[PDB]
Image (cartoon, coloured by chain):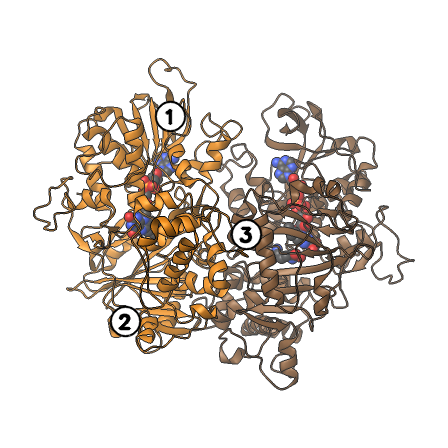
Chain colours: A orange, B brown
Amino acid sequence: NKNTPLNSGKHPDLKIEVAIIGAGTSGLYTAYRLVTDKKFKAHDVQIFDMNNKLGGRLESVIMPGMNFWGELGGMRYLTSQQIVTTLIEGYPLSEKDPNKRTPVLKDKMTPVPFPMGDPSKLLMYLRKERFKQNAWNEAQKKGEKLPTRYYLNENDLGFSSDQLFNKIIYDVLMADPWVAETYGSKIIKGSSVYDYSFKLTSRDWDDIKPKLVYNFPNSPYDQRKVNDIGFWNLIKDQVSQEGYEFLANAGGYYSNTINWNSAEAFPYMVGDFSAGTIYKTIEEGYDSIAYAVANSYMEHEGACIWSENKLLTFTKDHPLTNTHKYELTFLNLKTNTQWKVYANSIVLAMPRKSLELLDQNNFFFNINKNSVLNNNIRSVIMEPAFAILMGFEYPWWKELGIDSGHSITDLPMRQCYYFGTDPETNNSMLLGSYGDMETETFWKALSDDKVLFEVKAAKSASLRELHQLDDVQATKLMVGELMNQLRELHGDTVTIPEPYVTYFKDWTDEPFGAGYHAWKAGFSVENVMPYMRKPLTDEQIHICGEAYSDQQGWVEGAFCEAEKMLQEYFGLDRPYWLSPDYYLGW
Amino acid sequence: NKNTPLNSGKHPDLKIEVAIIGAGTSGLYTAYRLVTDKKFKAHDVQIFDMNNKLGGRLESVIMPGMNFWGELGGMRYLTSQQIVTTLIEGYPLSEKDPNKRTPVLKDKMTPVPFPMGDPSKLLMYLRKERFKQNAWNEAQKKGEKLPTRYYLNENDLGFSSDQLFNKIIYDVLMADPWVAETYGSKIIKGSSVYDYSFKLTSRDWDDIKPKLVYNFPNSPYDQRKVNDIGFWNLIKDQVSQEGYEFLANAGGYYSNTINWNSAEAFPYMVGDFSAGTIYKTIEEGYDSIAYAVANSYMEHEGACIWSENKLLTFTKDHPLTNTHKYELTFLNLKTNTQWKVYANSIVLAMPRKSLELLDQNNFFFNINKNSVLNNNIRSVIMEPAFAILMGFEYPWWKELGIDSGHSITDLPMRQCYYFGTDPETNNSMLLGSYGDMETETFWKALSDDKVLFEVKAAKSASLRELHQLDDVQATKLMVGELMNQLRELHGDTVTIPEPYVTYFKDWTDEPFGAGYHAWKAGFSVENVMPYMRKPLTDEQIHICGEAYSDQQGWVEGAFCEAEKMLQEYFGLDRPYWLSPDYYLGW
Ligand SMILES: Cc1cc2nc3c(=O)[nH]c(=O)nc-3n(C[C@H](O)[C@H](O)[C@H](O)COP(=O)(O)OP(=O)(O)OC[C@H]3O[C@@H](n4cnc5c(N)ncnc54)[C@H](O)[C@@H]3O)c2cc1C
Ligand SMILES: Cc1cc2nc3c(=O)[nH]c(=O)nc-3n(C[C@H](O)[C@H](O)[C@H](O)COP(=O)(O)OP(=O)(O)OC[C@H]3O[C@@H](n4cnc5c(N)ncnc54)[C@H](O)[C@@H]3O)c2cc1C
Ligand SMILES: NC(=[NH2+])NCCC[C@H](N)C(=O)O
């Protein structure tokens, strides 16, 4: 299923209609929709990627001794994300029996719940105090306010990060009298001082985000749109810098407390409501969604993914202006030779860093001409991520009654996910994932070191099998220091043995430069998104993907931006399998 | 004296020997030494800068109502920095009667001691606890260990940041048996648990830094060169993450605690031993040293600083290869037109960001040829800095008995300097913050906002005078939030009135991309420095300046790298006025 053919060759002066650059989720989805709806024959729609793999930031791996998929990138989806959920599960989403679902893609994909674990057993390790994640709720059940080594404002004492986040967003929303009046029925103060909940929909958030005013009379930010305030600016203002320190650390990496757009951060933090929805993954690896869309595209005659082929530049000044608006110059990495593709539409299905790495002197990127394009490319923050998969001969975490889920710390490692145990071998997988709150610089000095971790034999994992992964091992300095932090996080009551295998991915590396993106304060997001899907009025050049999506951090963001671009400029209707009530904006 | 002529015009096909690109301290010093020692006629040595002023990261300003110089960039020097000190004060430095000193530069420069303030009155505000900076010493005088809201290891309890830093460096030095044996006499444990001191010289540090081994058998970093360990990596290892949090926040700007080269950080923290030396500035503004060096150069007929002229690219492939190795293409910013200069030597007197903004496709930078150059350009961290100068109608800080010096906080502002009061007007100047790497994103969302602070009339400061500075005002959001943090830092015992004028510079802006630079762990600094002063053996192309100096953060670093380059490639001797015992390395 994951052996989708990739062509590392070239075809000098190939003449097509639509060049898609990026074999990530948005680029694959674009090519799949175009050929499946028969807008073009598959030989006129071609995908190019510089990688030796399709999928981009989805990359599922199997490590010797562990007969289940680890994730280097994307792990999971939410069933409220209708494009990715329908593509995985079939339709309609109402149908609760998976056997009565109608598949959209042929590839077998087994949806399984994402294990979230037990707050009673999962750890929070902050300023050297070891808590269970439920510690705040247990105190509140006994009429107590849990003390921490953070000096919160007095009115926040005993709040958890979840509860305090909810109270902040509630307070900011309800202080805007227009929001209070129009949406108060969906912004809910429960009975307990700690209980705040939201029933605001995607549609509601789209009405709110551009209008919401910060109404706090002696704040520095008073009477400004929440859109124009950084989320760290806004959190400090509401709960003091000690409050920000608490939320930034206790939130974890899945929680986004960088100084990004506060209007956009609000829905990110409290969800687009329909709370029958849960986190799931794919038994065969989350990258299966990319392989399934790619294979659906590749089953049409003339379909081709050109791998190890890097776009350098593109021009309107070429010999074939009579048949083709654009000449694209690709670098065939295997031969180090340049070749030309001729096309009438270009889809840049790639993030901010990838755009910046293209020739900035051509007609499209030239900053002397297209100052608006360049400003809007710079409208999103490139948030670093690293993934380190570690294989142990046994699940040492079970000694603490931990099955699954995430432990969270202010230590530089930030967070570990206890991924699974192979019931035959007992070999067990931990994910370390980090990058936020300055931890990139801590880890970069260690991951840049030249001396690699050496693989070690375990059950069903021979040196010959493991030596195939020599190249993708973490550094010994990074493994040693992470092991040190895991011992401090879990405490002295559990012995943590050395791992036998690791897998390391740095998503800051070119061409990605980021794990995910975040809208900056002070940009009109509702206007930048349509702009990015077709920057120049007289050019059939489109940007799509997660980076300029309004579901940043998510495959659904990449799919939604591609889908909007398809319906706007490629004359496609909503897919039959996609509910018309799934909101995609203007 | 600061009206040094700048030529914003062009001279198509100008034919010279030495093109210096960067009218910063190093570029000015290069041009001054070359023409003063008559290595070249002044018409054959030309300086080019894209700015509309000389000085680079030295920029002194006067604000209406305040009849003294504020500093946007460099502020002060140490009398152990012999090039900058001799240039300012005259020679020799042994002569302690200033009337028996022989001036080196004619421009009037009045050295005045840098006011350091009173640790009894200066504030430290950490995790919401307000201390006087002397609090740790006062506790130690009463036999006590000052408690803080940081959970230090038990062996560090009651230590100040200074004392704990000294202990860390002592412990690491003395654990290397070769360092213990060879240099133990200069690495001194005093009687009190808190007392550690060093008599290691510039020369001693140059022997030590490349050899020093981290000898800690339980550490992840054991048996690695201290050179190969990030300073945050090393500090956490020695005093725990809570210890790093204490040092990073309590240190201030005086401390560099980013994850940079530990071998280089050691002397940065504990000095090149040479006590009796103090901090000074120049009454006429610290940028006076730049104007003095520039004017000495510009006294020669044919000398020219080409301002508002930006180097784009340079090539060996041009019509005049018989007389001139290199053709330089400059962009004349006033006309947006390109012009050519022909030269046999190129001096890039510019930081990392400036080099990266040049054409990366030419013979020199092209990564297909010179991957080694590119790796060495990336050997230093670009540390962000900004400057916000604020003018108040009175020195509100005097209510707390504060004359001068720095308050330090874990609030995002990090540090403020109480600068001066105009005794006629009483209008008084704060340097609000430089921000830093951690806090760049907190402040950037506010400084990028479009609504600028509105100037307000004060004594000897009319609206018409102030409206000339409309362009360089901080944003309302940045001024309001900094004022909020100043109120929290100082407490409710002082009322802080609104400022009437501000001055904002962001040193992350192109072409600087940094306030200062920091060597990365894992680079052989002793080998990169000589490499950068002449990267290619067959080319008369040189890099000098602070960025690849071993006195990063300092004018002295820029002067020393220019001086070494001059003695190595341009046939100059040490200047007559520079003591032969001033160590300048290999
Ligand atoms: C650590 C991590 C965790 C994540 N977790 C989740 C999660 O749990 N759930 C989820 O739904 N999402 C998650 N995501 C996000 C998800 O992986 C991405 O949003 C999505 O995969 C991005 O799709 P895209 O189309 O933007 O392209 P990308 O995946 O960014 O792919 C872009 C492609 O363009 C190629 N390219 C760039 N420049 C060129 C060039 N010049 N020539 C040729 N090819 C070029 C690249 O090689 C790449 O294949 C996560 C991301 C990361 C990093
Ligand atoms: C906030 C702050 C505080 C500081 N405090 C002190 C202090 O108290 N004492 C001290 O001694 N040092 C201090 N420093 C450092 C000191 O200011 C610098 O180390 C020093 O001025 C750097 O000089 P340089 O020769 O490296 O060049 P720079 O100052 O970096 O000048 C480089 C020049 O190159 C030009 N340039 C770049 N690219 C091009 C191009 N393509 N074409 C043409 N021109 C180009 C730029 O316009 C610029 O003028 C401070 C720095 C900052 C930011
Ligand atoms: N390693 C560095 N460059 N540190 C920057 C510190 C600030 C600089 N020394 C100054 O005097 O303001």
Circle 3 is placed at which residue position? B443
> Residue furthest toward the top?
A322
**Is the CB of mark 1 within 8 Å of ligand 1?**
no
Mark 1 is surrounded, within 10 Å at the Cα level, by few (under 14), some (14 to 19) or many (20 or more) other residues, namely many
Q: Nearer the viewer, mark 1 or mark 3?
A: 3
The residue drawn where x is 71% and y is 49% is: B559
Classify mark 3 as within 8 Å of ligand 2 or not, answering yes or no: no
Crowd band around label 3 with a 10 angstrom C-alpha radius: few (<14), some (14–19), many (20+): many
The answer to whether the residues at label 1 and label 3 have Cβ atoms under 8 Å apart is no
The residue beneath circle 1 is A328
Q: Chain of mark 1?
A: A
Which chain is indicated by disc 3?
B
Above or below B138: residue A115: above
Discs 2/3, front: 3
Q: Which residue is mark 2?
A: A121
**Mark 2 and mark 3 on one chain:** no
Residue B59 visible (yes or no): yes
Q: Position of residue B322 (x, y in %)?
A: 66, 23
